Amino acid sequence: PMPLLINLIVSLLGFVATVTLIPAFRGHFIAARLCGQDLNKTSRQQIPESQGVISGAVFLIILFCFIPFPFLNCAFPHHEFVALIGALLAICCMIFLGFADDVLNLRWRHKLLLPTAASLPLLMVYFTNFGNTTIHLDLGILYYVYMGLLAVFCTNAINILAGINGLEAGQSLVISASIIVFNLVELEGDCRDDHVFSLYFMIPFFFTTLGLLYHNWYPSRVFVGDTFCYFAGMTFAVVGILGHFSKTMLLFFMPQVFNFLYSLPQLLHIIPCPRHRIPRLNIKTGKLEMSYSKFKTKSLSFLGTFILKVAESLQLVTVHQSETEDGEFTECNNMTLINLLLKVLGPIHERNLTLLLLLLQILGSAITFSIRYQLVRL
Amino acid sequence: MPLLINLIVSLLGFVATVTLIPAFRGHFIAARLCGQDLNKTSRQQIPESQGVISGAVFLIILFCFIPFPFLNCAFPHHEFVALIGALLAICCMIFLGFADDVLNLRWRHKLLLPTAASLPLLMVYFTNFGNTTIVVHLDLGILYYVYMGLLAVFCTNAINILAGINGLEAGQSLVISASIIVFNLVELEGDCRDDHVFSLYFMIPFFFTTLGLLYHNWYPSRVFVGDTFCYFAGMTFAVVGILGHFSKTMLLFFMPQVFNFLYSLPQLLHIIPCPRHRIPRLNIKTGKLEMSYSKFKTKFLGTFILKVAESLQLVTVHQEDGEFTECNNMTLINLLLKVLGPIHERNLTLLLLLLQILGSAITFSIRYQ
Ligand SMILES: CC(=O)N[C@H]1[C@@H](O[C@@H]2O[C@H](C[C@@H](O)[C@H]3O[C@@H](n4ccc(=O)[nH]c4=O)[C@H](O)[C@@H]3O)[C@H](O)[C@H](O)[C@H]2NC(=O)/C=C/CCCCCCCCC(C)C)O[C@H](CO)[C@@H](O)[C@@H]1O
Ligand SMILES: CC(=O)N[C@H]1[C@@H](O[C@@H]2O[C@H](C[C@@H](O)[C@H]3O[C@@H](n4ccc(=O)[nH]c4=O)[C@H](O)[C@@H]3O)[C@H](O)[C@H](O)[C@H]2NC(=O)/C=C/CCCCCCCCC(C)C)O[C@H](CO)[C@@H](O)[C@@H]1O
């Protein structure tokens, strides 16, 4: 088809634009203090933050320039068009929200609320165009709720699985590429329009995020930040909702779902939650070791002690106990998939750990394809 | 029923703006998004880019209002896509303005990006209306679209350069928005009702959110609106004008801004040297704003333009190491100060708002009487 060919062309041009512009704007970001230190390395220099915006920006540009080509010599159908524009409005609002969130570092209340507001246009489009709120049970209003929350989830599910160089953009590239392959396979199948739409929004995302990862990859010269996390989350939520494969998509979100649940006791502050739960480097080794959350044992609530004991029993959390004059203490293992891989394999270098998590992501995607198409497993 | 709900949510949004602007002050100051009131003695920092909150609220409101018009209304996808496309243009303008303020992009970006962000407006205009003919009966064709594109840019920047005194940006934007609201209501009973009810949908919430912003921005300014609000407002106006089919009437409402943009044009083009700031210098003793000047070496076209201006009495010119010329900084503000001498900041803002209202009354008189 011509629309997809044109789309791929503008997407590669956008990849070049991203790789080019990211260094071109470095002075601006440094000047306005939109930067952060590399916590996992000994160096203390600043690195430009929220580079996702640039990719995001390019992304938007591309799609704005690509809208007409599907409708070439095509009573104009305003519904396909409104799907496009509504999805783009959702993504614009999510990019803007992530950029504002990186400049201001809003509290979690805002981080959860605002992606839902920004996902409303998605629900408008879904209701005017498709509207099928059935899974044989009719989910009704709940279904819309789901879609809303989906957006939030994605934006934040990628957001909390972060901290090592190239993980956010990397795992987002794996997810986007897997969704692209799924779209292509289904492209010959029953639902062609939904999946060609998913492609329209994925391909440029993949290539712009690739331009971003070029700089973000270890050693990280740039950081993607909440801008990229939110942007990616909403793009995925869009193609999943308006593509009608949100189940398959969430299956692709297996590492992120597992890490979000495994972190859930800390995110709810049942077990104390540090401000950063990244694996903290060992200066002698040069590799990343696990990171811990320490606290007075007595203060901990009953539910917290129960969850911690069950986790220790399952061999998921490392627990240490030490005696101090002021009070009794019990160290806990920071509960994030990264610290869990480090519990399983001990010290790992940053680049190798990122590669390992990308590998595990690919395994998750392969599992999803096997489920979808009755393939052989392992 | 739809307009009544629009007004309700717009007042709720006014409350939301007035409440949130101080709620987020900590965030803006902590992230160094602030600036010093150059025209006041104090040196403290004032939070910048507060138009991002109002703007944000604005978007929220409209996102929530979208359904009320289509209540049990072959769904009308064209009306719906116009609402969405306008919202998309406005989102990209709020976002681009906020990013511009944080990063302080060069003029190249400032001009290019509102055109890109205005493309969805042109797409909606082509799919829905597409009329590229004006009676003057000439089918402008592609140029028409160009116009619309540039219109966006112009507005976003036309309000942008007319700035620097407490409450001028949001104030003049409120006058323009209110004038367009009145015009929409007058034409509401006339031939074109849908266009003007659309313009109202977008204008009422903008008016009330911008009002919440001006509450804090008014002399003495406790906040600043910044490129965020300038871009946001400019694009909301360009939208309602384009998709409402009254961009000529609108631009007539942009009378002070057009005059100030053209009067500044020889400096903006660097024919006459242009300082980074061209606001009026406060007089320490007087407590009132006098004119400001650009000083540069006298030793081709620029000199002729300055002589012409001197003859016209629009620019005041005074002529060590070499001959230097202290030309009067060419902005409607410095021109009002050249006509009336020193004026206090609040009084000068009020005066420019009154002149804006005079321009709007002129526009109404031309159109109607
Ligand atoms: C809580 C949490 O884990 N936050 C993360 C999250 O916190 C955000 O951090 C960000 C900064 C972080 O990226 C820094 O790490 C450094 N860095 C970055 C890359 C890199 O390669 N190397 C490096 O050193 C670098 O300095 C960088 O500035 C930012 O401050 C967010 O505001 C902050 N809060 C949240 O995400 C909220 C997150 C709220 C999560 C709530 C989830 C809600 C989902 C609900 C869905 C439900 C309805 C289904 O990210 C951090 C890692 O990037 C984690 O350490 C931190 O723990
Ligand atoms: C050149 C110029 O005049 N710049 C302005 C413009 O410059 C922008 O400044 C901005 C900040 C400014 O708002 C400051 O004013 C201060 N302020 C404001 C009120 C107040 O009460 N107190 C206070 O202190 C406060 O500190 C604040 O930081 C910003 O940095 C832009 O990058 C900067 N450039 C442009 O707009 C470019 C604008 C590009 C103009 C070209 C557009 C061409 C349009 C073409 C359209 C055509 C197709 C029809 O705005 C300034 C604000 O007054 C002016 O003084 C300044 O002179």
Image (cartoon, coloured by chain):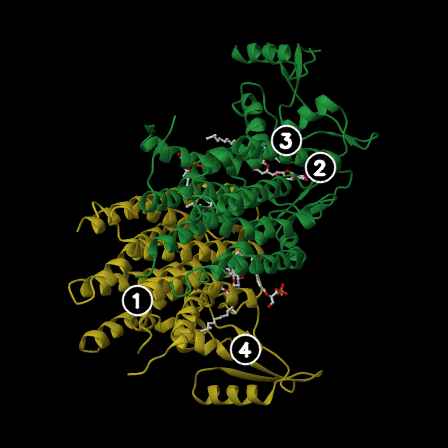
Chain colours: A yellow, B green
* SS state under label 3: loop
Q: Which mark is residue A268?
A: 4
The picture places residue A308, in percent across and down from the top left corner, at 52, 86
Q: For mark 3, what is the residue?
A: B277
Cβ–Cβ under 8 Å for marks 2 and 3: no
Residue at 44% of width from left, 74% of height from top? Answer: A260
Residues at marks 2 and 4, CA–CA distance in whole angstroms: 52 Å
Calculate the distance from the C-alpha at mark 4 to the C-alpha at mark 3. Answer: 50 Å
Q: Is residue A358 left or right of residue A190?
A: right
Amino acid of disc 4 = Leu
Instruction: Specify whether residue B103 is in view.
Output: no
Front-most of residues A228 and A312: A228
Q: Are marks 4 and 1 in contact (CB under 8 Å)?
A: no
Q: Is residue B299 left or right of residue A333?
A: right
At which x and y percent is residue A200? 28, 55
The part of the image, by quadrant, that contains residue B333 is top right
Label 2 element class: helix
